[PDB]
Length: 168
Ligand SMILES: *CCC(=O)N1CCN2Cc3cc(C#CC)c(-c4c(O)cccc4Cl)c(F)c3OC[C@H]2C1
Ligand SMILES: Nc1nc2c(ncn2[C@@H]2O[C@H](COP(=O)(O)OP(=O)(O)O)[C@@H](O)[C@H]2O)c(=O)[nH]1
Ligand SMILES: [Mg+2]
Image 1: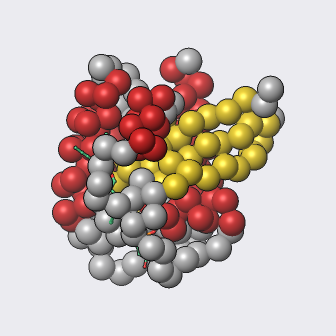
Image 2: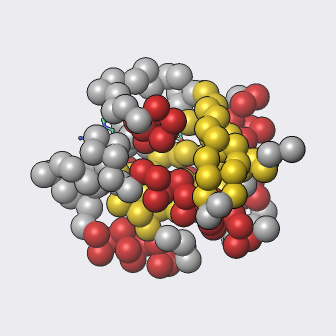
Image 3: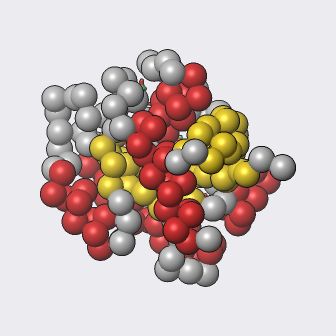
């Protein structure tokens, strides 16, 4: 059957996890998406000439351990670590999420990409150097995105797919 990639999008409330995922699948920018709705989404893509089906968990709600999140964390192949460039706390929260994923994987070498979202906004509080430093510390790529303009959205997901290929 068609190759699949199981992806997980994680990050603080409000950073744009749903908006990024909706842009990828639908090519529309959502100004409001219910923060409680945790679901998976599927998209057929072609990346470096390979047709595949992405299976993407948009994490949401507060109720952490849940049938769905548990199975995607245990079986997920790659993770997008999303913060917003106007949300310093969301950047500070990234290390927590990376630590929890590493503990589920019992591994230091999990495919991940750091995503700094909301690049269209004036109110930057996390500088690109802070992002780049963090990603280099972790050994992973950094991609700047805007779900509003769509800048970097494909690049983020495709880079994650390329990172999974490099690992397996
Ligand atoms: C605004 C609502 C929303 O989008 N979310 C609420 C905050 N969530 C934070 C968050 C926390 C953890 C944890 C822990 C301990 C994890 C997680 C879990 O649950 C299990 C294994 C690995 C990790 Cl990283 C999150 F994925 C996560 O991101 C979701 C965010 C959703
Ligand atoms: N300006 C701008 N707003 C965004 C961007 N991404 C998300 N938003 C907005 O930020 C809010 C939170 O987005 P959402 O996708 O619900 O975040 P989630 O809680 O991580 O799923 C919503 O009002 C979105 O429209 C972006 O790149 N730029
Ligand atoms: Mg959401």
